[PDB]
Length: 260
Length: 260
Ligand SMILES: CC(C)Oc1ccc(C2=CC=CN3CCS(=O)(=O)N=C23)cc1
Ligand SMILES: N[C@@H](CCC(=O)O)C(=O)O
Ligand SMILES: N[C@@H](CCC(=O)O)C(=O)O
Ligand SMILES: [Zn+2]
Ligand SMILES: [Zn+2]
Ligand SMILES: [Zn+2]
Image (tube, each protein chain N blue to C red):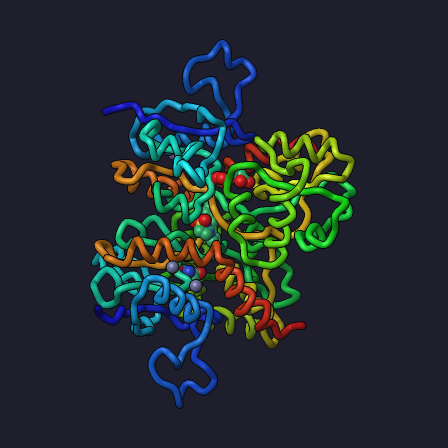
């Protein structure tokens, strides 16, 4: 038996550096929802594992010209990792090159505003110009807008792709900071899960507004032909059915929420 | 090549007989969310198909003594149908014997009451005995309560399994009728999708109360070894991303609303 290499991403509250990480070793350096989930998946499937943080800090996209996959998807496609346990969105283009388990969490694209921003919906954002808006610069949210045929989102993509300066951000943290420092003049499009988490964090100056734009899931991903595929899929189902996944969401989102 | 036999279930608004069904033939007799979904999946996967209503009128459970599966699950397991396109809940015990596509719709177990029934949560139901409560037979909701170790749900099952007269019903229609005729003395445990639909239909005398008890999905199911498995899975993802699944929910839930 070989130790399973797990690719993941520093994204709060999924995977975070522990405050005393420099004094700890291996998997013990990290904490969060996905750290807890990895330990359980490994236990139920009967494997030893090593958490690794994706080298380029990205989720996964295929470059238009080079056809090279980056991010966690790349690590799986190119054989650098055996499994991805992360807030990695199940999409058709990804499912064509890797396998996903059944989803372990639901989400949809959503709008983050600085409190008091006169925006209720995606329609509102598309109808006006004073408030800028954007997405994570690589990921499923950007691709949703790029590939969309619905009029509001098509109009939104047409604005976003040509906006100057760039409305796209390198990390979720950068998007959140931009909202917080822009005095209501920037709104951020991000997954409801991350939006909901930030809403419960000091300085309690952001909120989710409106309905989700779509409905999808995060899944645990393996390269095609992985011997882990079946066991991992069944483990996610078992953990959902036994109430663990709901427990972990409560633990990391709400139990220690900082906004009352 | 060969006409694909689709097993499905008469369940509003997934598969319903059209008002003028007696003067109609084959697939044309039926309408609903899953009728539309089957047409789309067939188109993208390039097959012809025959919709057939499950013989025993059940979703599917395994007899504890004989180990024989019934319902749509049994029809797949024993080779009577090629695919199930229905509101069929993805579960561990089912995933062990059949394959499921990625989910096409999210749901959770929920409570249906007659309007004015003094009940707000599962906790509320468990703490009393004047209001009876039950679930559908041979489905995933029953299994949830049978298997649950969460104290509220365990107490609910202990009551439910022994209650006299029986609190379990054969069909959703039977559960709904029981609520409507029991003058507030029966509450029904059913999936949020079905509950929300019924709440928007005449005579507008029921409602969903409390949050969902769990979070899960319906999937398209195929027998193990099926040549359709990959194409069906990819087609479900295609339809979600194209916005078609969202259009279909709006068509069959919101647009069919009768209660203003
Ligand atoms: C925890 C999990 C069991 O709850 C979920 C998560 C997501 C879905 C889901 C719903 C609708 C569409 N899609 C698109 C394919 S998806 O991205 O695989 N998931 C969905 C359902 C239930
Ligand atoms: N979960 C996304 C990243 C975040 C986003 O795009 O909003 C992905 O897998 O690409
Ligand atoms: N969707 C359920 C049936 C409805 C229920 O059990 O509430 C199943 O697949 O068994
Ligand atoms: Zn466990
Ligand atoms: Zn289509
Ligand atoms: Zn297609």
